[PDB]
Image 1 (cartoon, chains in turn red, blue):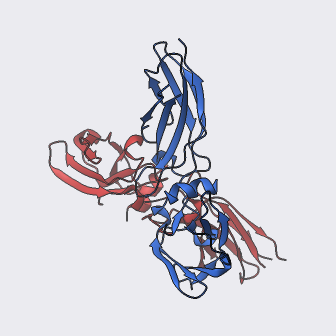
Image 2 (cartoon, chains in turn yellow, orange; image 1 turned 90 degrees about the vertical axis):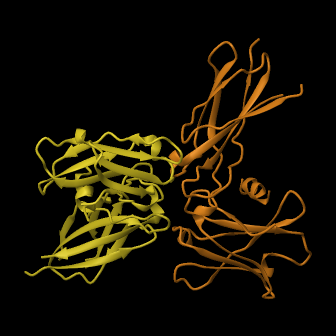
Image 3 (cartoon, chains in turn cyan, red; image 1 turned 180 degrees about the vertical axis):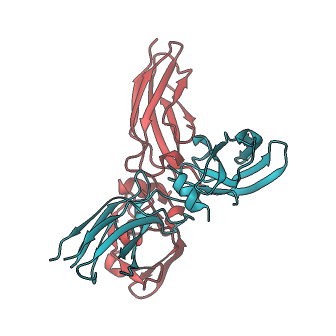
Length: 207
Length: 209
């Protein structure tokens, strides 16, 4: 599920992100070690003048061989944008991670969905998609469309601003294979974040 | 309704507000002056790399003699929290208002809806249920306030509901008395400045002996 987001967000440190501004997921990665599991680490955090609390850690494998420990904050401590102080120490108390987080600065939406490309110009292609499901202020979401084709293929990018979930592509090379994908993120109004992953592609052949 | 919220803010400068964090209305109020209409003012604004542009002013009567001029920015210039520089000038070119704001600094939500009140216990206990204002993003960040009033000195008590939860429990209500309930919403202040919505439509209930 979020195995892809963390993989992408892996851009070692303790990394956090919110999917729909009413949640927060933090995780870190390290070499797998015999006998070491989520019971060997304490993940604590605190809201403005509220006693530190611990988060139920989780461990999961990775496509790369290191392990990932994550914590999904209870929905009650992620319903406002108050700063979150996070502190990860070994079950023995040995310090490892310490930082602060503003849920509004680490956005990472799900990829767009319902991508479809109608070839409606005996040349021009029409692309239509949907915003990441269950995501507020869709008008703030900006998109990036990928246009690739395959001899030595090529790829090109198309900016979609102000929240439009559709576009038209022209100057596409005739009789060729084209694969399209869409990814989004907040325009950075007041939302810090990163690009979502590419949507599920959709290829078409031009006449 | 735009009048509803308008009053609330007037509670005299250039006042703007956003219902859903993707819109924006600004307005000011001044004394009625013969010969003075919306054509006597210029409402300019600039954002991003956008060249300055004007907004269609409108004029309408308030409930107190003074007149209200308002601009409703296009959806296109209201799809980001980036800074916006507003500026109201008289047609003569004489400055009236100047300010820089963020759409997220002036949230004035619609009022909650569906208030249903019903008794539970027998020693004077009623529970209040309602839902957040329609088409409103980030409901989890919405706080509430319940106004509980009885009509002979009368009474009024406020219940500050938690964060996002839309339930309520009122206890210790007087005997056979008519109680009226109303809820008002405010975006918690995660990072959204603002003001309280208007009282939702009231709900009344009669208390047993």
